[PDB]
Amino acid sequence: ELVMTQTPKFMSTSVGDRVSITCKASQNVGTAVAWYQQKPGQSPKLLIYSASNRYTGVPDRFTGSGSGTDFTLTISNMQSEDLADYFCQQYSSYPLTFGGGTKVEIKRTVAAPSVFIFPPSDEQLKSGTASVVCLLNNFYPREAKVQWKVDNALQSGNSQESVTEQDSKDSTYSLSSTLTLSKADYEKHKVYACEVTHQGLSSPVTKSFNRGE
Amino acid sequence: QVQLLESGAELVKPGASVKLSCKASGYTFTSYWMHWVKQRPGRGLEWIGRIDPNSGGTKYNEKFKSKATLTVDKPSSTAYMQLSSLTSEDSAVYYCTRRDSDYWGAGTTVTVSSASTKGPSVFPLAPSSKSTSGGTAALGCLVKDYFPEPVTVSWNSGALTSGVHTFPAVLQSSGLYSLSSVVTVPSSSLGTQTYICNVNHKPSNTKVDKKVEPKS
Ligand SMILES: CCC1=C(C)c2cc3c(CC)c(C)c(cc4nc(cc5[nH]c(cc1n2)c(C)c5CCC(=O)O)C(CCC(=O)O)=C4C)n3C
Image 1: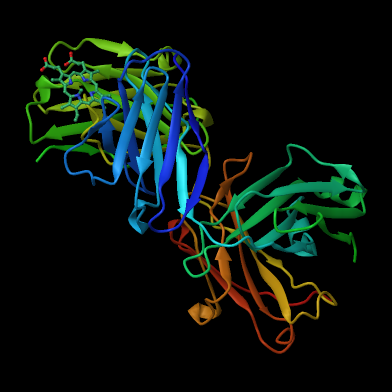
Image 2 (image 1 turned 45 degrees about the horizontal axis):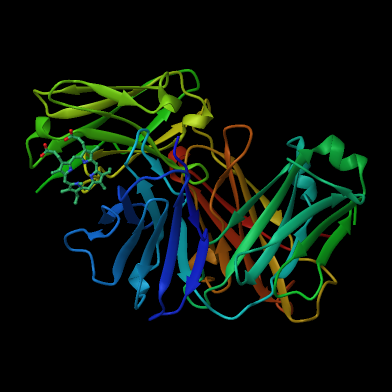
């Protein structure tokens, strides 16, 4: 199928800035490309079709351009109401395919996350599973790397991450990484550490505890 | 005005099938093709196929060839998409949209799970003791193994809102949901100020109040 590669995945901006989003086609699609905007809990909304045709009702702020294999969606004089996801789509050939999307967010100064780690608590153990939680609080930008290490052993496939949307007041993010394992495994080891890497930190921050305090 | 009315939300058990609806109005149903699209936060948007309401002719994305079946009912001006033998991979929001994608349905969220209504378990995320004297500590409640959605969390019956972060519910390899709610407070209030998370799970008519304090 024709693959539409969309960049950037994320883009932070300030009111009035110009936003530029790109979609590259694996093969020529002429000018059969559309651009859409999508906000949480809503269906996509058509912005541009035929690569540069602004759909009825769409603000002059939105301009589509390009042809062949290189397409651009430009949002001049960015407004707060433009904070949303944007997707391109080619309809030159079947199957129709969509770009991976770009989430336009609010720019602010870099802020390092405050890290905290939480033990499973005896109460949960009774369930048979142990949950270890790591918290990255109020950081920016969203890019963050969290690594779990049990007794200095890098974990894989047993953790899940959740991130909040930008705070309405300070525009930061918060993230939780939860390491799930059986009580058996949890009791087998002693050292539990959460190592965090973020643009705002001059070096990785590690928070840890030893089972049984 | 043109409108495409979709189901909204469907719960499907693994292996079962579900038929989604998309009722058209405000225009002549048979004059425009109808597209169906799938959306997952990770996979993104995918074109499933299209159907010409006038002829019944269809075209599918190879990826959904054995998964979706598109049909229409002229009398009711409604388009349908049959999704068969579902797995967790099929959980997503499905939309129907007219030929030019100028008009879209609101989307039908499909959740594939074998779980039955179940209230959440609530565990304390205790404040680190003898941690940072920076006057700021973090504590919270781990809300896990509940079904279906949603669950709400407040602190001290709503009196505490500043610094509260309640994370989006994630899915575990069990078919049950889980999430944490945290809050940062003055490291000087610990031991003196009481912190209680109020968890409500309307689906099971279950509510939990849990005091989170330093562990002994
Ligand atoms: C989802 C992608 C998509 C976008 C975005 C799109 C945009 C679009 C709009 C919206 C403002 C309008 C009025 C037309 C405008 C048109 N669009 C089409 C025809 C099509 N347009 C299609 C797809 C398509 N069209 C497809 C697929 C067909 C073929 C289906 C068919 O056989 O009718 C026609 C021809 C139909 C006719 O009058 O015989 C016009 C005019 N198209 C090009």
